[PDB]
Image (cartoon, rainbow over all chains, first blue to last red; front, side, top):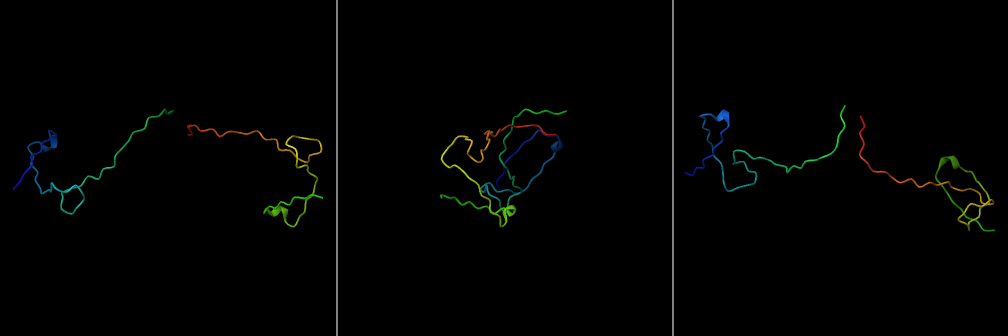
Length: 52
Length: 52
């Protein structure tokens, strides 16, 4: 069995362990990965505005 | 006689013949010419504006 260790200092995981099955060979959506993060690249806009 | 025929689809011209004398050889106003177009060429203006 093969494992990958992850860490976050975030608080709600204080002494909390979660574990599940993931696949490290596919980058594409498939019914066999725990979750997929659909990401749209994002850009900013800068302009001058009047408000009240 | 020379003649020029022009047609339009506007209903306000239904079955109506309009005649006059014109002078199709000048590009300047002249007392015998029928009608002249006072034409100030306005240029489109592109600009962001605040509305409400």
